[PDB]
Image (cartoon, rainbow, N blue to C red):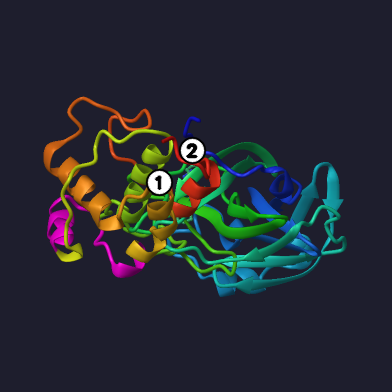
């Protein structure tokens, strides 16, 4: 029993973290096989950043402009290229700890684990959702760029995020591992802000199912809703609209618990209208939205408590 934000074991990723230095800028990169990935802004100084031209900054560097350290082993760069907002550095050694992996561009509302690193050195790990506004509520200090986000499925690490920057509100922005920002952001010091965010409706409902799997039913009711009248209600309360595909996704949890997805939607609808009456769900005073349907199935028992 219990229900906690839980990240994936970090070992496989830890053995991929290196330090990348260009001039007096230092950050993290990811070493898989004979390449190292890192934020391209490592070639910038504080002067450059606000209006940099990466192409023009980069042609001005050589391979030995880049210093790559793996523990205390110096790795020699023998090639480099830019790919969107990411540099790929080719090194003279293939990482012996490379795990099976792929890269994935994750969708808003999905979750990943983050290995926070400084100076190539893993310091901590937490779990984050991709917000609808394409931010993540991370925990990151200066030097944390190049830290990655990932999921693990069997033996295989699906890398899906690398950190670049922090926004005025204190949330974080970055790219997938082909260098393409999540959201409308750029790696320039520009007057860019988090857009308005929304609550992830699919995850809230998933987490309500979690509560029922672990034995709690207090927030249910006798009513049902149309998908459409749920959405009139959802919008008022700044929840994402529920679609039929989100309904389909909850089938397996609907089936484990015997609560119809639209009956659970009427439950949520009532919760939004009335509050939680000083009560808690899975230990929270508030509705939670950073657990996905998959996260619930992964962590909860396959046998419901009653
Ligand atoms: C990652 O290493 C950090 C980002 C970070 C810090 N805390 C959470 N996340 N690098 C930030 C760099 C690069 C970004 C590139 C996009 C535009 C803004 C730019 C800001 N960065 C800075 O380092 C600015 C910090 N100011 C500063 C002043 C004086 C001395 C050091 C740093």
Q: In this rendering, is residue 120 above or below 77?
A: above
Q: Find out whether residue 48 is within the magenta segment.
A: no
Instruction: Reply above or below: 106 against 125.
Output: below
* Above or below, 74 relative to 212: below
| Disc 1 from disc 2: Cα separation | 8 Å
Q: Would you say the beta carbon of the disc 2 residue lies within 8 angstroms of ligand 1? A: no
The magenta segment? 229-246
- The residue closer to the viewer here, 254 or 295, is 254
Picture coordinates of residue 156, whole percent (x, y): 70, 58
Q: Residues within 10 Å of mark 2 (few under 14, many from 20)?
A: few
Percent of width and height locating residue 268: 22, 46
Q: Is the Cβ of the residue at disc 1 closer than 8 Å to that at disc 2?
A: yes
Magenta run includes residue 239: yes
Q: Can residue 194 be seen in the rendering of this structure?
A: no
Q: On the rendered structure, is 151 left or right of 232?
A: right
State whether label 1 is within 8 Å of ligand 1.
Answer: no
> x, y (%) of residue 218?
26, 33
Residue 233 on image: x %, y %: 13, 55
Residue at the far front: name it: 306
Give the residue drawn at x 38%, y 32%.
282
Q: Secondary structure at mark 1?
A: loop
**Image quarter hosting the C terminus:** top left
- Please give the name of the residue rendered at 34% of the width and 55% of the height, measured from the top-left corner: 202
Q: Foreground: 1 or 39?
A: 1
Badge 2 is on which residue? 5
Query: How many dots with numbers?
Result: 2
Foreground pick, 255 / 11: 255
Q: Earlier in the sequence, mark 1 or mark 2?
A: 2
Q: Is residue 291 above or below residue 217?
A: below
What residue sits right under mark 1 in the picture? Answer: 290
């Amino acid at each position: 029993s219990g229900f906690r934000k839980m990240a994936f074991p970090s070992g496989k990723v830890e053995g991929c973290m290196v330090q990348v230095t260009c001039g007096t800028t230092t950050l993290n990169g990811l070493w898989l096989d004979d390449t190292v990935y890192c934020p391209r802004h490592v070639i910038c100084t504080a002067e450059d950043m606000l209006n940099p031209n990466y192409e023009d900054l980069l042609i001005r560097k050589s391979n030995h402009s880049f210093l790559v350290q793996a523990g205390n082993v110096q790795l020699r760069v023998i090639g480099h290229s830019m790919q969107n907002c990411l540099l790929r550095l080719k090194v003279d050694t293939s990482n012996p700890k490379t795990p099976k992996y792929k890269f994935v561009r994750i969708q808003p509302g999905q979750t990943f684990s983050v290995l926070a690193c400084y100076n190539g050195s893993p310091s901590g790990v937490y779990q984050c959702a991709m917000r609808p506004n394409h931010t993540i509520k991370g925990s990151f200090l200066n030097g944390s760029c190049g830290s990655v986000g990932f999921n693990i499925d069997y033996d295989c690490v699906s890398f899906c995020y690398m950190h670049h920057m922090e926004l005025p509100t204190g949330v974080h922005a970055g790219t997938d591992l082909e260098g393409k920002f999540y959201g409308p952001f750029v790696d320039i010091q520009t007057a860019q802000a988090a857009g308005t965010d929304t609550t992830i409706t699919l995850n809230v409902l998933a987490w309500l199912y979690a509560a029922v799997i672990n034995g709690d039913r207090w927030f249910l009711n006798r009513f049902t809703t149309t998908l459409n009248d749920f959405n009139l209600v959802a919008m008022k309360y700044n929840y994402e609209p529920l679609t039929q595909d989100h309904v389909d996704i909850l089938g397996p949890l609907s089936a484990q618990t015997g609560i119809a997805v639209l009956d659970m939607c009427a439950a949520l609808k009532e919760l939004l209208q009335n509050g939680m009456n000083g009560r808690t769900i899975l230990g929270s005073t508030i509705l939670e939205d950073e657990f996905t349907p998959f996260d619930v199935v992964r962590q909860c028992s396959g046998v419901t408590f009653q």
